[PDB]
Length: 185
Ligand SMILES: O[C@@H]1[C@@H](O)[C@H](O[C@@H]2CO[C@@H](O)[C@H](O)[C@H]2O)OC[C@H]1O
Image (cartoon, rainbow, N blue to C red; front, side):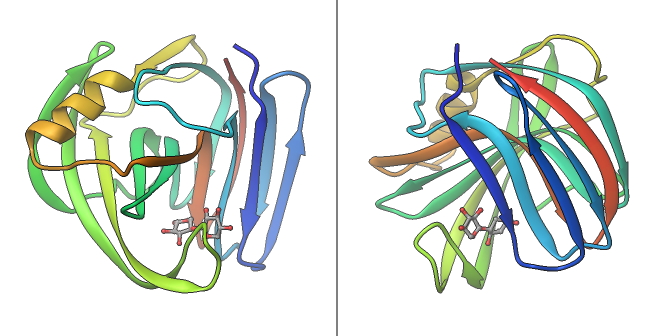
């Protein structure tokens, strides 16, 4: 499918050279950053969407995630489906596991306090995570069957909000450097 949303957010720290390429393609070169999220996807997320991507380059030198990323409002929730990472594997409060698209993911919940959100300003919100147990190899056509994650989260009392915001296949980083090139469809 054609992507219709371009996400390019940085808190202003360091260098974040994000390129909005042709179709669903984008690349990022980052150096000595603060927090940032770059990615392509859809303006309105869906719990039924099947996301396809191919990360031609996934080369983080530090803390960075290659992850499905999105938000819902009512309640405000930031969610992730992490396929690969750099030096740090994100974890939180363990809820259980889900097998999807050839991999096994651990399910975690964390909370952010006085942090930036899609609404602007700062607030406290919950984060839902599905983190692969082992890094998924990159360079190949990968699929994330999002429904499997949504259903598993629900079975663990992790309900998403009623108002869906954007949903993208992103490159997130925190105080690191690196490069990525990803195509989303
Ligand atoms: O849409 C943008 C959001 O992506 C941003 O929220 C931060 C995203 O990075 C995560 O690591 C943080 O938890 C989260 O605060 O807020 C700005 C908004 O424009």
